[PDB]
Length: 311
Length: 307
Image (cartoon, rainbow over all chains, first blue to last red; front, side, top):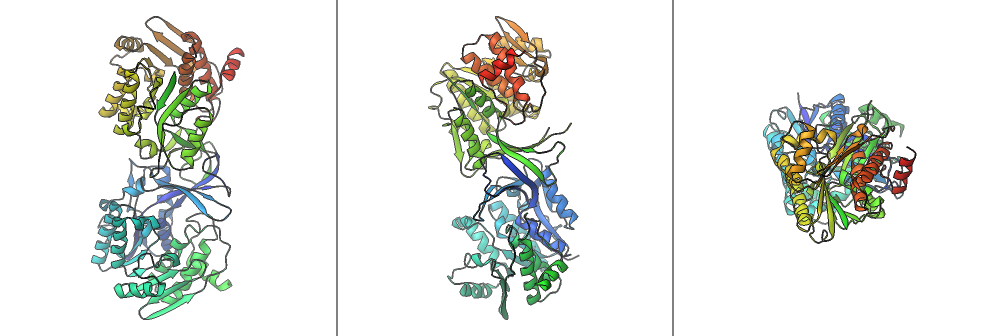
């Protein structure tokens, strides 16, 4: 009955079929593919066998259906996904440069996703929610923050746990309203999971150490740092440790952080200790980047176990 | 003597296979320049008539493919505003035997307003064409109203193609906007199925007659595979349809209109203009792609001769 819930953008991704393919010339594209950091995160949670749900908004179109179908089939409680007739399901077109850099044409802010208001958050859907996960990338409007704030109040009310992944767009930091929202969340966060490049973003300090130790002082219980292709680290007032990255043929990093986080949250729900959870989250993130597609790199528990072993 | 239009500019993404669904991973072709006003204006420039368009796109590749196509074809694109915070509109389509996923209303093209209509850009506009499909929001209506009145007050001619989605007729504000345009229309170009839409009359003969009496000077009726007709107080005549393998009619009606307007600008009498329009429309349907079916004068005349 205990459930892990997340909230945020759900969209489909349409990928360029060839590297170097431009946006301003006819070509071949592949998709749609289920996507959206919160959706990818929750999909990893369900594939690990942990009952979960997601609060989102999609339009009444096939793009919205493919996401709902995928999540539902994978075991996710999809009741929290409202369908908006007068809106188009968010999307994202992506191309690849020879350098490895990606280019996107996003439609999220002015699509169904950016419609999610505090009213789409039903207290009845979060009754059995003991753990709520927030994606920084979701906070791009006041309506979004309200929904998130409402949900967090409801979950902490029933004694739930709050985790927060600051995977935002740096630009958002130059907006006072959104700047506060992020800090507001950080203050109510028990589990903080920034990537190496985001540790200082929400910190008054200038060094990762001070930043991490600062977070713990503020009230954060755990800080998990994803160091891209350099491993990751676990930080708690009582302990501290790190694991190394696995050497893999990177193909698509789009959802490596979401998968890493899904594995961490789910593994911890399954009783794993911080050390086991960390190596698994790391292995999960590593396995994810090896497959093309935002949500096509998720893994089952023993696939992660085996990945680790064979290495 | 310049022709202008206004409205949605977007890119179309096409399913690679017939029967291909929107909810399964597949292969798609695109983007392809699209949007009724853009298709219409492209056909105009390709026939050698100076023209321009007023629209809004995003600061992205989808916005660029449209601007570049029109510019390279000779269209005056100074009227196309680029909106940094908006995504250029798009449309995914799949066939059967038809179905779409549209992002227009809440996209860049849906932000077009009176503010984006520069009276100065229309200073030398002698003919302004309105696509009914463009009237989907108060702001779009305000843009159209400002543009039409400027041109009308400057002695220009107004053409109007009611290529609307029947839905809009159930919305009073949009219903009233369509009448606004009709009220100031000189050349009305409804397809056979749109003839009675803006008329209080129940029969087409009576409707057409009503439009001429209300102020319209010319009514051109697009009858798809049944040819087309021309109606004015001075005369009435019809042409038969050209039998052709129809592949995609998404822009056939736009090309027809573009041909009629451009040809009249070139000095064609009503009969010759109707013949080229009819032929231009026939040629457009034979190809897949919104704007991939526009033709140049040589093609239209070569097609005609062969028949």
